[PDB]
Image (spheres, rainbow, N blue to C red):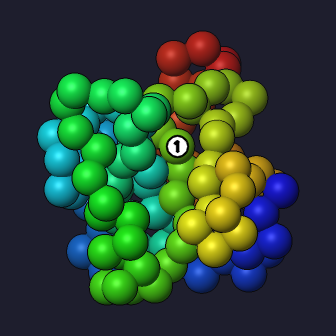
């Protein structure tokens, strides 16, 4: 569980999650994405060997905003999703996933949670 999730600061500043449901800033990846919990910056992170992209936008986001938390998009299930912390450096959980995703328009139950 993320310890930063307790003190999760969200920043609605032009946050507009795309009609694609997800896709990162830098590269053109449809998967392996990291949706920032704060301002809603969607980035990604390739799984070792990838031939589509996965550049270092995460560090840039730490340079720009400094918010080291993002949801691993694509792993979103009715139960929950995977989250990565750049601050804790670990794959972390969030006891407010549903709230955060719901505030993002991300409905886990939409496909098969109802
Ligand atoms: Zn990317």
Q: Give the residue number, with chain letter if any, for mark 1.
A: 72
Quadrant assignment for the N terminus: bottom right
Quadrant assignment for the C terminus: top right
Q: Between residues 69 and 96, which one lies in front from this camera angle?
A: 69
Q: How many marks?
A: 1
Looking at the image, residue 38 sits to the left or right of residue 14; the answer is right
Q: Which of the 4 quarters of the picture holds residue 39?
A: bottom left
Q: Position of residue 14 (x, y in %)?
A: 25, 74
Q: Position of residue 46 (x, y in %)?
A: 39, 38
Q: Which of the 4 quarters of the picture holds residue 112?
A: top right
Q: Residues within 10 Å of mark 1 (few under 14, many from 20)?
A: many
Could you tell me which residue is drawn at 34 percent across and 55 percent down? 42
Looking at the image, residue 114 sits to the left or right of residue 37; the answer is right
Q: Between residues 50 and 29, which one lies in front from this camera angle?
A: 50
Q: Which of the 4 quarters of the picture holds residue 8?
A: bottom right
Could you tell me which residue is drawn at 74 percent across and 29 percent down? 79
Instruction: Check the image and report above or below for 97 versus 37.
Output: above
Q: Between residues 39 and 1, which one lies in front from this camera angle?
A: 1
Q: Position of residue 16 (x, y in %)?
A: 26, 60
Instruction: Check the image and report above or below for 93 versus 57.
Output: above
- Outermost residue on the front side: it is 49
Instruction: Check the image and report above or below for 55 versus 48.
Output: below
Answer whether residue 12 is visible to the viewer in this image: no
Instruction: Check the image and report above or below for 110 versus 4.
Output: above
Q: Position of residue 50 (x, y in %)?
A: 31, 28
């Amino acid at each position: 569980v993320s310890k930063y999730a307790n003190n999760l600061t969200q920043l609605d500043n032009g946050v507009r999650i795309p009609p694609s449901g997800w896709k990162c800033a830098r590269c053109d990846l449809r998967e392996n994405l990291w949706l920032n919990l704060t301002d809603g910056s969607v980035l990604c992170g390739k799984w070792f060997f990838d031939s589509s992209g996965g550049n270092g936008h995460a560090l840039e986001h730490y340079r720009d905003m400094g918010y080291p938390l993002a949801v691993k998009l694509g792993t979103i299930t009715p139960d929950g999703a995977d989250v990565y912390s750049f601050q804790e450096e670990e794959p972390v959980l969030d006891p407010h996933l549903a709230k955060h995703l719901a505030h993002f328009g991300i409905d886990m139950l939409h496909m098969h949670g109802t």
